[PDB]
Structures are given as structure tokens and as C-alpha cells.
Image 1: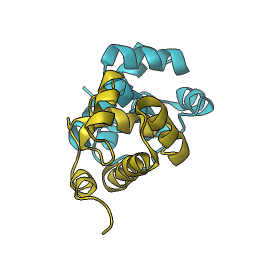
Image 2: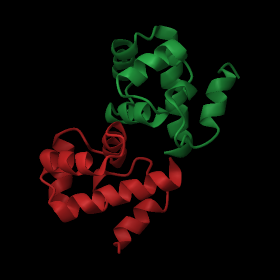
Image 3: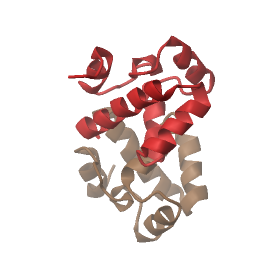
Length: 89
Length: 88
């Protein structure tokens, strides 16, 4: 396993009301910027992932534009949502 | 109360179900949704979630997007709300 333990913890269970910082790749800096833009719970970011039809490029660009995520942070966030959806959606 | 279409939707993960599997989304509404990019139920779930599950704003969005009447939007909201309570 090459994912983080934080990715593994997120994809292991339904997300419920978990905050946005529970997503892999979303540290405190990115999480605050997301919260300032209304994306305060992980499920709101899932919503954007789903509205973008789970498209990696669109989602990772959206994350970049919205909170300034770098390539690794956006890859990690995407992969965490992608694997959560494969498990639970 | 609820339709069997609702109960069937809320009973299981939606996976790749088409948008027409959502309660209230019939053939006419589904066509309009697909034309606008909402071809699978999970894309409408996405909009529901981006709107923070807000009933008024989601039902208004659905009316504006595909022409859903009050009953159709009520049925579609309720099926997404109950699905989220079970699986999200």
C-alpha cells in the first residue's frame, strides 16, 4: 500500500459529516481555503467530484483554482474520492 | 408515503444507475437532465451535495434545470435525502 493512512482511514467507511480536512491531500491550509469558499464538509467536495462526472482533470483543476492545491495534493484528494466512490457509491 | 421507485433507489448504492432511476424523474425530465449533462443519478446527487442538501435550493435548481413540478422535485429530493442518510 502506497496511499497514506489518512487516505486509508477515509476510504474505509462512509464519510458522514466528516470535515473537509479528512480528505487525503487536504491539509489545514487547503482546508481553511475550501471552508472559506463554502466547501466545509468532505461531502461537499464529493459533490463537486460527482458533478464533474469524476473527471480527474476537471476535478484537479477545480481544486487548484479553488484552494491552490499542488499536483500531489490534488492527486491525493482525487484518488481518495475515487476510491471512496468505488467502495460506497 | 413513497413509491416503490423511491424505496428501490434508497435500498442500495446507486452506482452507475441512470438519472431516470431517481424517484420523480420520468422520461421527459430524464431527457432534459441528460441533455444538460446529468446523465447518471450520481451527478444529481453531486448537485444535491454541492448545495449542502438544502431542500429549497435543490428543488428550485431541479425546476430550473429540467422543469420538474413540485411533486417531481419533492420526490427526487426525498429519495436523495434518504439515500444519503443510509449510505453517505
